[PDB]
Length: 160
Length: 160
Ligand SMILES: [Mg+2]
Ligand SMILES: [Mg+2]
Ligand SMILES: [Mg+2]
Figure: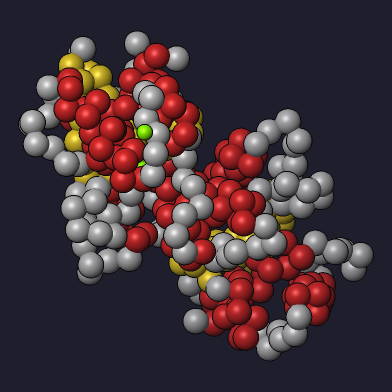
């Protein structure tokens, strides 16, 4: 398969949220979340920790040379947070590029289209999570859509 | 003086625009611009060129362990152009953090107010240029404000 590290990047600004990742190593899919929440750190300081956490994973599973598929950062609710998130998303890419074999921005609409995930924001979150829960890679309780999106990005990229 | 590498980052989408840089190495101030303009490329590829250009400079002048002072990205013209510039700015920082000993964002308003620079964008450019031209470091007729702004960021930082 194409060696892909899929990332759904988040600065973990709210408790319980984090950067979603997914990759395949010898047939086996690994998924998880980097839960870097800390109210005494800025978005950029928490992004530093997320980079270090993904470098640690890249080392543990020998992922050097995997291509980075990362969800496109877009304009959110408020302007200023979206620019912050855009800058932090960039920092994250720049810090691991070279360890990874370049990167591709994956628009949310494109990976949703491939999986036939259509509907409004809430509906798409549920459907993405359903697809992840159907695989058994996480507990049936799981409500972490950051992980689900990273997993659905991976499978889309493997198809391409 | 702290060993500061001052950067005024731009993707050079327009002819003549460049990423400006200024630093002090063995007591001599060096200033210049990375003229990355290339209609053949996206802002991201041009950003990658700029990273590699600054990487060459850090090597040539043995600048490892210098601290990065980089102008903050602000929300300007278009929503897309804002996310794009903010994203490429973050890429540049992430790509060179480690070669540099960390970084600090320098708001346009703070270095400008330190140097008594104010007005509309065009007015600020002329005053930024006057400070650079007054040093004698560049030719008399220099109109490269990207360079002027990086130099003024350097002296603002050195002052701290
Ligand atoms: Mg996302
Ligand atoms: Mg500037
Ligand atoms: Mg005035």
